[PDB]
Structures are given as C-alpha cells and as structure tokens.
Amino acid sequence: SKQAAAYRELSLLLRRPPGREAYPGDIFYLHSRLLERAAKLSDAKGGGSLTALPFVETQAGDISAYIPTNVISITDGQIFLQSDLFFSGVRPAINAGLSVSRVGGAAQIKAMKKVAGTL
Amino acid sequence: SDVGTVIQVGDGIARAHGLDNVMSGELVEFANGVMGMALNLEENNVGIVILGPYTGIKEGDEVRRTGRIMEVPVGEALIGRVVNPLGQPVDGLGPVETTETRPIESRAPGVMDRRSVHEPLQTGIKAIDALVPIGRGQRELIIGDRQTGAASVAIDTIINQKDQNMISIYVAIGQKESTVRTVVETLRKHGALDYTIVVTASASQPAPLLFLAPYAGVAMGEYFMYKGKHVLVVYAALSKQAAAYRELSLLLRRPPGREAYPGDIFYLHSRLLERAAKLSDAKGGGSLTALPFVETQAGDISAYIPTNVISITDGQIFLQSDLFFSGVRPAINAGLSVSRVGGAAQIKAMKKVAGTLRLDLAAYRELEAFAQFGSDLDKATQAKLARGARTVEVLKQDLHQPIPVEKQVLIIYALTRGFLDDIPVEDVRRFEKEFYLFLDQNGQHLLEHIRTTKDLPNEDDLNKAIEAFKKTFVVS
Amino acid sequence: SKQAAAYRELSLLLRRPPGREAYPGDIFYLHSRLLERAAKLSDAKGGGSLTALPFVETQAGDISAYIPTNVISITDGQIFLQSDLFFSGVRPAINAGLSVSRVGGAAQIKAMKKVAGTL
Amino acid sequence: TRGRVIQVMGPVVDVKFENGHLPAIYNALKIQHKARNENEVDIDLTLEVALHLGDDTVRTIAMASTDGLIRGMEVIDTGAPISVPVGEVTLGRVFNVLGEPIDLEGDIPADARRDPIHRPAPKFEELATEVEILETGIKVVDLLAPYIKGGKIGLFGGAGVGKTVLIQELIHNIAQEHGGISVFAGVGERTREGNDLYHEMKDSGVISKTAMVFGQMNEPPGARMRVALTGLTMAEYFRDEQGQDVLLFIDNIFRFTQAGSEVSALLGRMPSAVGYQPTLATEMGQLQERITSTAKGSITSIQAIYVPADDYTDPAPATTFSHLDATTNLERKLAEMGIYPAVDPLASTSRALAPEIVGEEHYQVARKVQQTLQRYKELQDIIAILGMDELSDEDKLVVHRARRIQFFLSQNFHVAEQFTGQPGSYVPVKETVRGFKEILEGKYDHLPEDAFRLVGRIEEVVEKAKAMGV
Amino acid sequence: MTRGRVIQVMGPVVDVKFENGHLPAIYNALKIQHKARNENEVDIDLTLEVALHLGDDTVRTIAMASTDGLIRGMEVIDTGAPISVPVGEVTLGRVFNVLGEPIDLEGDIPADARRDPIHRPAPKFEELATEVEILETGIKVVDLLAPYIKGGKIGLFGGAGVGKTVLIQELIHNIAQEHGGISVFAGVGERTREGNDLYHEMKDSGVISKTAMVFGQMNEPPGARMRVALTGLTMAEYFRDEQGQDVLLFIDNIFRFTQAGSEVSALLGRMPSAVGYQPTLATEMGQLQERITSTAKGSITSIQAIYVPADDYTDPAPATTFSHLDATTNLERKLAEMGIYPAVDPLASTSRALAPEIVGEEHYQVARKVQQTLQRYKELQDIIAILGMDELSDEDKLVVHRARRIQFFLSQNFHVAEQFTGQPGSYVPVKETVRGFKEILEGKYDHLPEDAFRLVGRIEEVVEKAKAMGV
Amino acid sequence: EYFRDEQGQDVLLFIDNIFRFTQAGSEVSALLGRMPSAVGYQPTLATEMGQLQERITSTAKGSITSIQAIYVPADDYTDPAPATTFSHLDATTNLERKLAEMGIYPAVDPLASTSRAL
Amino acid sequence: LLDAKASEHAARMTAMKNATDNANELIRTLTLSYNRARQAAITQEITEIVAGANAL
Ligand SMILES: Nc1ncnc2c1ncn2[C@@H]1O[C@H](COP(=O)(O)OP(=O)(O)OP(=O)(O)O)[C@@H](O)[C@H]1O
Ligand SMILES: Nc1ncnc2c1ncn2[C@@H]1O[C@H](COP(=O)(O)OP(=O)(O)O)[C@@H](O)[C@H]1O
Ligand SMILES: [Mg+2]
Ligand SMILES: [Mg+2]
C-alpha cells in the first residue's frame, strides 16, 4: 500500500491522468508484475520455489477499497487481522471468517489435516 | 482549392490541410470512397469526422469537397426497409430508390408554426392511456430498469398503430445487431414492419454514425410531417448517442466539462427533440411524436443525461423493479410519472372517467404508507384505502395484450362509479376479463357509441348493463 | 465567500493553477491577511482595538464548503443559528451547544461572569 | 470597415479586421452572403463581439446556426450593440432575440425608436425602497411567502415540480388586474409551452398590453444568452419613459447561466467549480441589477429558477438567492404525495412576512402554521417505528392537525384543469388566514383529512366532507 | 524501402518514422529484430501494432511485449498485414500466446499452415440467427432465475474473491464434456498459476484434445492483454464459419481487456474520460463483442467473467458491457460472506430473458413467486435490523420464515468445490428445481430447521439432511 | 537537533498543529501547479511528512521526542492527513472536559499508547 | 398478575437495550460510508477541474 502511494506520487508528477482515488490506471499492473514472479517451478526447471507474503494496510477494516481489492484479485488468498480482536487481548487476531487459503490446503501434512477439520 | 490532404488519422477522426471553400457541416469524401463531415474549420486545418471504416485511410491521401451540407435520403421507398444512418440498406433487398434528400440539421418550428396538442395516441396500455396519456405531437420519455418491460412498451405502441394511419421510424442507437434483427422479425410478423422504416447504428459502428442516427431518423420523419402525415419516432438508448458525442469531442480535443461530457451535451438532445411538434392548420396539420427510451442501472434517476432528457421532454413514464417484483405489471410509478399535456390528449369519455385518477392514486400511495404505522382508522379513510386497492388491481395488464380505448373507459367507469366496491380485491382481474366477454356478447351498442362519438354512452343504460353483468358474476 | 469568488474569477482569467474548488493556492492567505488585522493593541501602542464580525448565509446547515472551513479555522469562534430552532419558537435561534467563543470569560464583566456559569 | 472569417467552431467565430478599426466589445456584426455558385448556401447571420485577440482579431458569439459559413466571408461592423424597438409598437407583438417580430402580423418600420441591449444598472441614489404586499390569491404564498410590489420573486425547484404551472397561474391571477404593462421572456424552455401561453393571452385579451420575447431550447447559446436582455430592455423603456408599473415574467433564468457555460470553453476560459464559467456571479449580477424599481417606476419581477438535481448548493441557485426579495421553494416529496402546488412552507423565509405588515393578525397564524409543520418533520422518523403508538396520545394531536394543515395548503388552479378535472379557485388573504386559524383552533378536527385536498375556501372543505357522507 | 526507424519510446508506445508514401495501414504488424552489435546493447525480438497516423511520416504503435532495451534509430520492418495466427484442426489440443505461437512445448506449427488476421468486421445484419433455446446447466439458481441462452452471451459480474472463476469452472465441468462440438478457452489478465492448473485438469480430461487454449495473463504488458481476446475469437470464428460447428467460448476476465486499453490510451495522447478510462471505451468493447454472435452457418455460446473494480457496479467498464449480454448473473460479497454459494443476487438475472417463452407457463409462475418473496423480505430487512422479528405482523412473519428457506435452498454444492470441502457436488435438473421451489412456496417443509436447506441438491436431500441432524 | 547532536542530551519538541503544516504544503503544491492527489492533497504528502518526522529519533548521543497536536479535518480519521500522521505515532494522550469538570487534573485518558509503548 | 407485571417491565427493558445497541452500530457503519462518499466526491470534482484546465 505504501509502494502504491509512492508510485502514484511519481505518476502525478509526470502528469499522467489519474483515475479512481487518484491512482493511475497502471496500478494493477504495478503489483501484478511483482506478485506474478513468485512460483513453484516444475522438475524440468529445477524444482525451486518462491513464496510471497505482501502486507496491505486498510483504513477502517474496509476490504472493498481499490488497492485491497486489487491485491485480493492478484494473490491466492488472504489472512485478515481485526483491530478489535487485537485490542481485546487476542493479539494473533485472525478473523477466521474472512480469511482463506486457496491453494494451501493440499500442502498441509496429513497429521494436521486429520485434526484441523473438527477445530 | 477544392481538395485537401490528410495530415492525421486515428480513432475515426482525421485532419486535412486545405479545402479552402469547405463549409461548416459539409460532406467530404476520401479517396477510399468513404464519407466524412467537416466539424471544425481551424485557421490552417479542418477537423473531419469519418462516416465509415477508417483503416483504409492513410496520411497523405486526398480528400474532396462535395458541395452538399450533411444530407439524408427521404421518401416513400424507405418504408419496409432496414437502413443505415446514411440511407444505405442493410436488409439485403436491393436499392431503396428514393428521389430527394433533407438536411440532417434543420430548424425546429417556431412558436407561431404550431398548434396545441389535442388528439390522442393510443398505446393500448391502460396505465399509460389513463394516467399518463400521450398525444400527437408530444414527447414522452420511457425510462425503465432492464428487467421491467420498458423496451417492449414502445414496440407494443408501434404495433398498436396498425389501423390509425401513422408512419413509424424505429431508431436503434448503439444497440446489439442481433437485437435489431430480433426487433425487425417481430415487426415483420406483425406486418407493422410494412410501415416501420427502421434505422440501425449497431455498437460496432464508428462513433460518428451513432451520433448521427437520431438526426437521420427525425429528418426522414419530418418529410412526411410537413406533407401532412402523422409520424411516430422511437429513440433507443439515447444515452449511447451522448457517449458517442463525448467520444468525438474528446478525440477532437475540446476540453471536457461535467464528468467528461462537453458543455454542448444538453443542446445536442434539445435540437433533436424540439423538432417533434404538432403543426398548425395553416401548415398542413401534420404531426410528429417522439418516444425516447432510457434504461437505468439499479433505477438511478439522478443520472446526468437522463435528467437532461427529463428536462427536455413533455413527461416521463417510470417503471421500477421493486414495483415489478411486488406484482405490479407494468411497473409504472404513479407519483414519479407525469404528462405535461394530460387531459387534452384524452377522448371526451376518458376525460370524464379518468380525470383525477393519477392524483387519487398518488394520494392513495401516501395514505397506504402512513396507515402501516397508524394504529387506528375510520370509515372514510378505509373507503379510500379499498378504492385504491381496487384501482391498483384494475391497472394491471399482461405484456403484448392491447385493449381498445372503448373497453378501457368502460372498465374505469365501473371502478370509479363504485360498481366494484363489493367485489373482493383478489377477484377484480377475473371480473374484468369476464366483463369484456360480456361486453362483446351484449353491449355492442355501447361499444359502437363510444367508438363513433368519442363520448360516454347513456348513463342509465350503462348502469343497467353493469348491474346485469354483476348479477351474472360469481365471486370466489 | 463572495470576495473569494471574485478573486477566483480574476485568477482563473489570468490563467493561474486551480485548487480545491478552482480556488487559487493563496485563497487561505487572502483571508488570513484580512482577518489578522483585527487586534487589541498594547498600551504602549495606544490601547485601541478592532474587532471583526464576518457573516455567512448557509443553504441548510452545511458548513462543509471550502471557504467556510477556512474562515472557521481562522477566527476565534462562531455563532450558529438553525432553522429547526427558529421554527420551533426559539428566537434568536442560537444553538448554544455548537457555538463557541475562545476568549469567553475574559470578555465579560464581573457580574455576568458570576451568574453565567450556572446558566 | 470590413473583416473576414478565420475560424468556425460551432457557435464561436473568429474575425480579422484589416485597417486597425477593430469593433468594440458587445458590438454586433453582420454576415450577409448570397451564394456564388451551386456549391454554397445563402447566409444572413449576426455575431456579438466578445473578446479581442492579438493580430487584429476578435472572438464573436453567433446568434444563429453557423452551418454554411466559409473561411473568407465578409463581415460588417454595425458600429453598436444589438438594438431592439421600444414603445407602444412592441405591445401585442412577439419578438426574437434580435427584435424581429416572429408573429405573422407584419414588420416594424425602419425609422422607429430602437434601443441597445447592453446598459449600466441604476445607481444607489435612484432606487425605490418601500414594501407593499401583492395578493396572488394562492393560499400558501399569501400566508407563507408574500410577494412584494416592485420586488423580486424567485420560484425554485427541480425538474417537473410545477414551476411553469405556477408561473401561468400567477399570470392568470395578476396580469388582468394589473394597470400597467406585462412582459414575458421565454429563455431556453419549451416552444409548445410558449405557443400555449400566447394563445391563452390572446383568448383572454391581455395580449393587447403584453410584449413577448422567446428564445427557446432549440436556439444556439447566443440567443439563449441575449433573449433575457432583449425583454429587459423592452421593460426598462416602459419603466423609464412612461413611468409605468411593469410586470416582468422570466421563465427559467437558469438557462441564461447554462448558455454562458456552454460557450465558455470555446471562448477559452478555464473551468470554475462544478464546471461553470469563472464569470458566473459577475455575468448574473450584470443582468439581475438592471431588474429593479426606481423613483420613476417599478418592475415587479417573477422568475422561475431551475435547481439542477434538487441540490440547492449548486452555484447557479446559490448565487441567485442573493438577488431575491422573496422565494418559493417547491418540493418533490409533496409533488409525489400529490400536494400541488407543492411549495415547501419553511424555505420561503416568508421574507415579506417581515413582521410589521402581517404582524398583528397574519404573522401569528403564519408562524403557528410553520411551528406545527416543523414539529411534524421531526416526528416523521420517530412516527414510523416507536412513534405511532407512543406519539398516539400527545403528539397525535400535532400530527392530526399537521396532516390537515398540509392538505389544506394545496389548491386547485385555473390553468391546471387539464390535470385536475376541476375549475380553479381564487382565495383572498382574509379567508386564508381565517381558515387556517379555524383549523388550528380545532373547529374541523372531525372532518376526514381527504376533504381538505385541492379546494379553495374552508366552506368548500365542509361541503366536500358533506358529499363524502360525513 | 519499406523500413522505418524508432523515433520515440514511451513505455508500451513507440513512434516509428517511415519513408514518404510507404506508411503502413492502421492495424499492420511491425517487427524489430536487432542483434546486439556491442556490449552496451542487448538483442531484441519485438512486434508492434500500428495505432495512429501522427503526421509527418510518423506512426504511433503499441508494443506486444516489453520495450526495455530499445534505442532511437533501430530498424523497423513492415509485414504488410495485421497480426495473423494459425487456424484449423491444427489448433486443437495446443496452447498459444497473443501472437499465435504455441507455448505447450509440443513443437512448432508448420510455416505454411493457414493463418487468419486478428482484425475483421462483424457479421452482417442479414446473416445473423435469432432463435432462443435454453441451455441447462444443473445450477438451481441459474436454471430457475437467470437461464442461459444457447448461442447467446452470458456475463458473470463480481468483485474480488467472490466466485467468478469457480462458477466458470463448474460450467466447464457441467457443459464441455457433453457439448460434442469444438471449444476455446481464452485467459485474459488472470493468474498464470490458474492457466497451468486448468491445462492439467483439461489434459487428463482429454477434453484438452478438442478444447485447448490461448493465454495472456497479468504478467504481460498492456499490448498483449489488449489482443489475446481477439486471437481466441479468431480461432473460434474459423470453426463457426468454416465447419458450421457450435462453439463454446470461455473468457476468464473481459474487464482486464478494457483496463489494458485504458493503460495505453494515456500514453497514446488521448484526453481522459470519466474515471480516467479511454474515450473510446464503448467503441472498442462493441467492436469486439459484436463478433461473438451466431450466424446461420454456426453458433457461438460465450461465457464471460466480468470484474467490477471495487464492489461498484456503476464503474464504466461493467456498465458498458451490460448492453451486450443475453444473460447476466451478479455475485455479491454479502451472500458470499453469509455462506451462500454460488452467491448470485437473484433479481438482476436478465430475468427479462427467462421470462417469456420457455418458462412462461410452468416455470415462470415459480420463478416470479420466488422473486416476489425475496423482494418483500428485502423490504423488511431494514426494520429487522433495529428491532428484530418481534414487531412484525403475523403474516409478515411468514414471509421471513419462507424467504430464509428459499434463500438457503438457492445455494448448492459444486463438483469443483469438493477440493475445498470433502462434500461431492450435485447436478440438479430444471424440473426438480421447479418442483422443490414449488413445495417450499406451498409450505410443505415449513417445519424443518433452516440449516437443512444449505448446500444440497434436490429437495429430498433437505429432508434426509434434517433427519441426519436429528429432526 | 543542535542540542541532540552537540550537547548530547534528550530534547523535547512541541508542534502546535501538524495539520496546518500539511495544509500549507498543499497550498504550496497548488501554487507550483502540481496535479492534486486524492481528496485534493499534494502528491508528495507522505514524502513531506516522512522527511519531517524521520528527523525526530534517538541516536547514540541523545534523542528528540515530540508532542504533536493533530486536527482531524472532519472528525474523519481515515482522511489522508490524519492517516499519514497516525502512521508515525508511538503514543497518544487525550484530555477530557468531563474530568476537568470533576476537578481531576491533568484530565488525561490516553488509551492507544498502552498497546505499543507500554 | 404481580409476576406478569414484573416480567413485562424486564422484557421491555431488554428489548430497548438491544434496540439501542443495534441503532448505535448502524450509526457507526453509516458514518463510515458517508465519509467514503465525501472523499470520493472531492477527488472526482478536483480531477475534473484540473483535467479541463490541462486540456485548455
Ligand atoms: N461455490 C463455492 N463453494 C465453495 N467455496 C467457494 C465457492 N465459490 C468460491 N469459493 C471459495 O471462495 C474463493 C473464491 O475464489 P474464486 O477464484 O472463485 O473467485 P474470483 O471471483 O474468480 O476471484 P479473483 O478475481 O481473485 O480471481 C475461493 O478461495 C474458494 O475457496
Ligand atoms: N397545480 C398543479 N395541479 C396539478 N398538477 C400539477 C400542478 N403543478 C404541476 N403539476 C403537474 O406537474 C407537471 C410538471 O409541471 P411543470 O409546470 O412542467 O413544472 P416544471 O416547469 O418545474 O417542470 C405538470 O405537467 C402537471 O402534471
Ligand atoms: Mg417548466
Ligand atoms: Mg478469478
């Protein structure tokens, strides 16, 4: 989110026409370029890996803002942390309802899979 | 000189160097055989709008003068065709065979060239003909909500003109071409195609043609209106023409305004719609009535272009999706819809029967809202509530089922003279169906009297017929 | 606000950059220059004074326009009159809760300062 | 001398003058051109000078369409602004922005007195400053928005709320009585409405004392900019030379500013707030300040003002407010409830109600009506959930009268028969003030609320309840 | 000579100057093939598409790949024709990119195979076919309220993370095995992971064998995302107009196409329109969507997922696409969070297309009764929020009682959602869908707990699920 | 900074209305003709705030700690000026007129500060 | 009857507590949406103004 603000500042100084929330039209591409470069390589390409954990700061828990929706539409899931939960004493405050891992379930170990369902 | 050379081409626009004697608003033709129109006469170049495919036009090509202000063919041969905004057929039946043209830009009739709207245009829809009547020479906006019947209203109106000596021009602006073909096959079946002439500007066409289409339709219509005929023009997605004009202006580098629309955006539709009129007797008495159509997203009336069009026309018909899903079909909102000629566009019988209906129904909606909270009610207010519920029921109708004005007046007479007060509300639709059958069988003198004199039949005979039917009727 | 409109018209006709509502960048400084000339002089300077009362007409209660916000930030207080109070029979119709004076107390005689607090 | 056309961009035209004799600003220019061949058209066009550029060049605003103009056409400087005839010769006729009669009754003679459209406004010493009430015969106004003789009246409202019907009712009720001249100016509104009004005036006979000027929606922005000034000049002549009392009706003076904003970008200005021209207040004050009464005569001006989206903070209405002595603000909620004329009873400041004149009898009734209607607004959100049970004892006494006061403020108009199925009514202020005092005293709490709708005198409410079967 | 040189480079946009009288047409492809003749340069293999004639022998063009390493003065070659791609039976089982080059690693396509230009006009008014027949999908809410038209256009609108891709994959699973004709998938602006994952699901399916593919994803520059859709459309058009086949066409996001257009309109020197989009937004949407139609020779059924930038449906791209679609389904984050999948908002549904013929007697009465009940519940929800159900009228309490049941029974268990949840999916016929909603509307199941209705198929599964729950 | 770097001591800096600082920056940006950012603020809002705030720190030879009074433009805490400022706070202190009336001075109720610092 | 009157006043007390809490939550979320709309409107207007000036 701070990178996006910096890029927007750069674009307004080059006088490019702003759009929604004064961000340039290229803001989606800014993050798509970056986040498309993490991958799981096939055995022909060596089998290496690169996994990314980008952070985005919302304003009042609003998930429907422009930048948060862009990044949600780029990544494979999100972990949503709630400020009230953090203040009540639950500091690892993961809102279980809104947070999801779209590809991670197949990568749990079987021992964890066998007990996570009831939890 | 009377030639020029293209210096820039792109996005359906071109600049030319030369053309010294070109007029503002003239026709020009490229070497390709494609046409254009001179909009801007800069000091040393000319801004041209391309009326066809521009991928064949290159910088350095020559451009020729034609000496003709922007024009369009007009004549009895356009009837039964499907035609492009330039008068070129697209239906595939051969050349149209016209013999004269009209300017697409022309002056609207003056204050003294007109007459007051005084004669009705029947849509066959009870709610419209009774609450928001439309007269010959009037302009009415139909603004709907995609899933509500707004689109079908005008096609039903055009088909209902089959015996009234109208000529029709359907103008499809920015529409999908398979929908224009679906409209043409619907009209064909109706032989309504045989009057309907049809102008098409599908969405794959360049912006200039979508900007020209309504002007071509109105210019083809006024040919008949100034000869003394009566014309009905329907404009489809008139906001797509506004989008096309915004595209053209931004590409010619005219600075934008509110949103990104030019400052001329009101004047565009003002020119377009002020040409509809009822001519005076000294002018031949012809007429031309316009029915623009707008589709709304989520029922938003506060859209810029729709508000401009509302401000230009003689009234609007509003159809809401909440009304549509609650069971009111057509979903016409009575408080929001008005006609600015109303009354003068109704036959005498309709004026006598339904002169207060719209105000009554709006007051009833207000009372119905207030009574839900209100923990008590008395006799007069309950009577008003019952009459309002019966009115709402009487105004319901099915799609594609037109009703003659003489039958409409008799049913509304029954409603407003208290003859339905004892019928249960859930029985009024079937009462009306059987009442129409009984009229067919037994009240031909009444129907003929209304039809030939435009006035109510004898009151006592009418009451007798109604009471005989009531005797024959069976309640659920 | 009408003086501000006149200046905005002049600065647009001279082609200067536009600001929040097409106002120029020095519209705040215009009214600061104006309103800071109202002062209470010290005795070595003569003891004279000059107090200013800018007046503004609202269109429903909205004070969120740019110029009203500027003047609100520059002044020492504001007196609020509301049509809801005016029609309910309370005239002069001042909204004592929303109104404020920051000199208050120091600008009252002893007799008033004695009895106004309980009121 | 002679100039030439250089650029054509819709309504704006650039003309170059050769020998250093540039036309002054606001001068009229003529382009008269007979076709040289079959590849041209004949032109007879008028332009108004707006700006001076460098290199001996001028920007002008066309008063008609610009189709057909060619670069190089000759332009004649007439030496003065647009000038229009004044005097008796204007009475009973219909004109356009240029002073040309558009009725079919002939043409004005060439030698007749002809006055210019642009003029400075009257000075501080010569202004009239006294308030006499004007009776309209309309209950809500005469109670809650009294008009001033010789003042300025504004009728605000968004689209389709009843401004034109109300203007026509005001003409119907006041013009025949008036012992002076009437002037009407149609500015950017419907030619159908203009034709209707002209024929109604003709049938009545009032047209023999009336001058009408029309520039309607179908005109280019220059005409819509200058038609109001044409009408104003015709009215100023009668105020000044004849010392007459004048009624000036202007339909939608908003179109004047809208046309200015249409041309502004082509003239080359930077946009102001909400896309208007930077000179909106200046241009509006130029016109508004000339419409005023002096020691030599009076102009009673009634203007209809369009509010673009019922948004009263829009700059055009917001600037118009500072020029009006009284206002009426029309409400869409009432229009949708079927309460016509639909005047919002608060917003009017009742300003003429300015306590003295009304002050003893009428002011107490007017303020008690407004207090009752203010309380009912606050109640309406409470009313729904909690309120209809809890309010039912204390506050239902307020609601029961507020419903009836609000239905009785509506009326049936003479010119609204095609909408109401009824003939109209004319209510004198005494009867209005009497009736509202009765309703507030509770003399009519028993009659059904629907009887109060669309009537005149309170006796008519009693009769309607009788007919309903009370 | 028919060669030019680079004059300017500004991101995706390049300016090329040619000799007099040899300017290329407006959609011509251009080639830059540069060998790094010195260690302070790099070699280049880039293709451009012409966009504007700038004046003074100069052309402005859009690059199909990254322009990094271009130098003012490189030599540019005109191919004389628009971008042309292989067509025919040779494309079946293959994966391609925007230029028509295979990317599946099964070898090249012969140099002499037929290839068709990417740009062409739409079919004529006299060639179009206008007949409506329903396309059964097995999804209750669709087949009841939003039924798809064989040969028409379908639009799946939704915000971020709401279910567009899962819904499209359930449609691919329910339709594409049975379809018998040819099929084309076009991935525009979506995840490259999802293109890999889809290729292997298809491969195993031997549905790869007919159906396979073109891709240009979120990693690509704007030029490729502006044209992959046209490439896929060209390959579909060949099968429609040369073999008479009925063709399925899937587009995983068509909003990214207009987004790519607006990312270059600025650098092309065009004034911004509302919300910053290009001024030609509607024209470019229309020229593309008009070529996806059914003629007499064959038919194209197109299913298009449409992103709404924020959860905002008035955004210009979705709002302009609304005019081209024969059915629409709008997905809502509110339902997706209440736990209702597919999460379709039932009202919008192009409930126009549904109504008249097919449904019009039997199914129309059930579909309208469902929409009327959900409309009245939606009216009450405002007061239900403050005071609950304790202040409703006893007949307005029944509306809530049955609307909850109807709203839960509209949700379903998908085959493709098994990999999230061990529950296997269900296919439900239209007759059973109409049957079940009719009984619920009559009150046959008013006693069951509302939880029995969630994520089931036929109405019998509700009974069995409540019995399992212990009622 | 002179006293932090030369005398090697802990200093206190008070800034009455950081909002007025950001507002002046916006006015200057309009004067210089830059394109406005969201809600009308200058495109360099975050950079300017960061350049000011990043010079207040503790070094090996002293520190600066700053008490800053912050005006929320419309009682909207998501507005860009309050958001960019709150991005740098380590602590907070709120004063209550209720306690000032109860006679409890200092009149403090400073809750957010508990979570980070303490 | 004494039992019934006690129960009625407790029931009304709990209902009006819950109603007040729900209304307060609604107020909070409505203020959030209002502020979002206000910010978006300001941005749209300023962008239109500057774009017109730039095109000029
Ligand atoms: N019908 C369903 N049943 C179960 N889970 C579902 C269903 N639909 C969606 N989900 C879940 O919610 C998420 C929706 O993701 P999906 O890819 O369908 O969304 P999308 O709209 O295509 O998003 P994006 O724009 O980010 O590509 C997935 O993580 C999936 O686990
Ligand atoms: N006094 C009235 N009585 C009945 N109907 C009215 C009245 N005033 C307005 N209306 C209705 O409102 C419509 C629009 O009024 P109009 O005069 O066009 O207002 P505006 O000029 O503000 O658009 C009229 O056509 C009429 O149907
Ligand atoms: Mg009007
Ligand atoms: Mg997706």
Image (spheres, coloured by chain):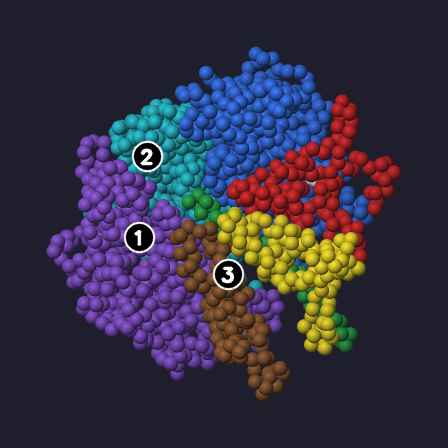
Chain colours: A red, B cyan, C brown, D purple, E blue, F yellow, G green
Any atom of ligand 3 within 8 Å of the CB at mark 2? no
Residue lying at 70% horizontally and 74% vertically, measured from the top left:
F100
Residue lying at 70% horizontally and 51% vertically, measured from the top left:
E446
Give the CA distance from mark 1 to mark 2.
31 Å
Give the CA distance from mark 2 to mark 3.
44 Å
The chain to which mark 1 is attached is D
The quarter of the picture where the C terminus of chain B appears is bottom right
Residue beneath disc 3: C28
**Residue closest to the eye, B195 or B441:** B195
On residue D224, which mark appears? 1
On residue E24, which mark appears? none
List x then y, in percent, for residue E375. Answer: 59, 51
Label 1 vs label 2, nearer the camera: 2
List x then y, in percent, for residue B341. Answer: 34, 54
The chain to which mark 2 is attached is B
The chain to which mark 3 is attached is C
Residue E408 visible in rendering: no
